[PDB]
Length: 12
Image 1 (cartoon, one colour):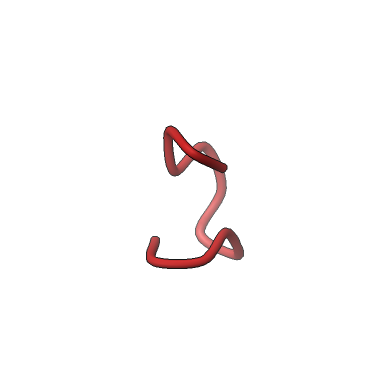
Image 2 (cartoon, rainbow, N blue to C red):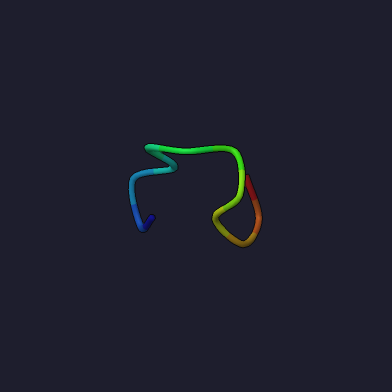
């Protein structure tokens, strides 16, 4: 998620 590997991650 720090890398926005899925849309559900915050900020992504």
